[PDB]
Image (cartoon, grey):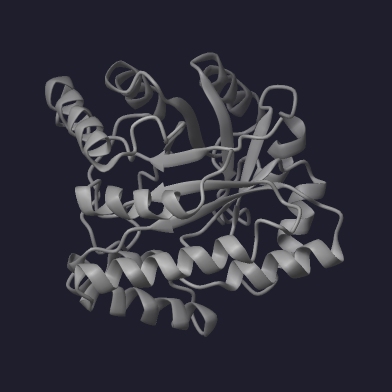
């Protein structure tokens, strides 16, 4: 009834590569995992769903394979793993979303995180499905229904509480670059009886971040202040040398693990490499798993 998993995020490959290079890159994924000791320690692959829109990102953003096309390639080169997915619901509508969700579960996906985009209905006439509505409407299709949890966001106790009452099974956190999730989950456990599974997301920060600034842009929240502290932590990680960068990352991981695992929520792990899978990212994931892994 709970995932109790370690999930590695794999963004679908670009549409232009074609299969011969798509599977070649997934074979590098496997060798880098074996080389780092992750083999057999990662149970799920999290495949995020696309935004077609360019959206302001520092990186370039080309068209990607659909979640289902990439998942078939993942199963051939990564035969141990199970499937988790991200699905945007705000642009579809009930009957179309039912067909899409049915196909995802039909093709072997074990859990789906419902993701909403703010959208304007003064115009944009034509209703989509709010992710909180899909949580209850499609509970008979999706057993593991997830939402995005941003602990630094200021109404998040009301927001995440409303999502769990509406039927959310697990919460997948934004990239965690501070221990804010500790105080959030403690207050959430004191104000509610909701005990959803928490997918703690940790993102590897390479030296490139000094120049591109991708992770700084992903976690941005104007005039928050707790996010500002996280943006400073990302910057010092990028400017740090590998030994100190790993130590800083793992101290953050250890504090999050220590302050969360006894609060009553089931805990799972979600590993991201926003710039791309690399051996230094996989060894950081292995170091964190050595301190604590769910089982």
Residue 251: percent from the left, percent from the top?
44, 70
Residue 140: percent from the left, percent from the top?
74, 23
Q: Is residue 158 left or right of residue 220?
A: right
Q: Is residue 165 left or right of residue 39?
A: right
- For this rendering, which residue is in front, 190 or 125? 190
**Quadrant in the picture for residue 17:** top left
Q: Is residue 127 visible?
A: no
Q: Is residue 191 left or right of residue 214?
A: right
Q: Residue at x 71, y 58 (%)?
A: 262
**Quadrant in the picture for residue 55:** bottom left
Residue 34 higher or lower than 216, as above or below:
above
Q: Is residue 126 visible?
A: yes
The N terminus is located in which quarter? top right
**Quadrant in the picture for residue 259:** bottom right
- For this rendering, which residue is in front, 151 or 217? 151
Residue 145: percent from the left, percent from the top?
65, 36
- For this rendering, which residue is in front, 73 or 196? 196
Residue 153: percent from the left, percent from the top?
61, 71
């Amino acid at each position: 009834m709970t995932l109790n998993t370690v999930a590695l995020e794999l963004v679908p490959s670009n549409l232009d590569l074609g299969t011969a290079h798509a599977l070649a890159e997934l074979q590098k994924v496997r060798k880098l995992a074996v080389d780092a000791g992750l083999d057999g320690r990662i149970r799920h692959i999290m495949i995020p769903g696309m935004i077609e829109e360019d959206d302001g990102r520092p990186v370039e953003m080309k068209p990607k394979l659909d979640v289902l096309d990439y998942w078939e390639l993942v199963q051939r080169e990564l035969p141990d793993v199970r499937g988790l997915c991200t699905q945007v619901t705000s642009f579809l509508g009930e009957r179309s979303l039912r067909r899409r969700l049915t196909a995802l579960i039909q093709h072997g996906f074990e859990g789906i995180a419902f993701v909403g985009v703010p959208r304007t209905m003064t115009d944009g006439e034509g209703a989509g499905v709010a992710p909180t509505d899909a949580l209850s409407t499609f509970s008979h299709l999706v057993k593991h229904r997830g939402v995005i949890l941003i602990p630094t966001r200021d109404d998040e106790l009301s927001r995440f509480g409303f999502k769990c009452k509406e039927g959310a099974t697990f919460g997948m956190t934004q990239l965690l670059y501070s221990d804010a999730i500790v105080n959030f989950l403690t207050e959430f456990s004191r104000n509610t009886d909701h005990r959803p599974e928490i997918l703690l997301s940790f993102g590897f920060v390479p030296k490139m971040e000094s120049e591109v600034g991708l992770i700084d842009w992903l976690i941005q929240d104007p005039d928050n202040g707790a996010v500002a502290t996280e943006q400073q932590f990302v910057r010092r990680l990028a400017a740090s040398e590998p030994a100190q960068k790993r130590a800083q990352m793992l101290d953050l991981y250890k504090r999050v693990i220590d302050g969360v695992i006894d609060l009553g929520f089931p805990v799972s792990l979600h590993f991201e490499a926003p710039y791309g899978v690399s051996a230094p990212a996989f060894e950081t994931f292995a170091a964190m798993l050595d301190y604590w892994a769910p089982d």
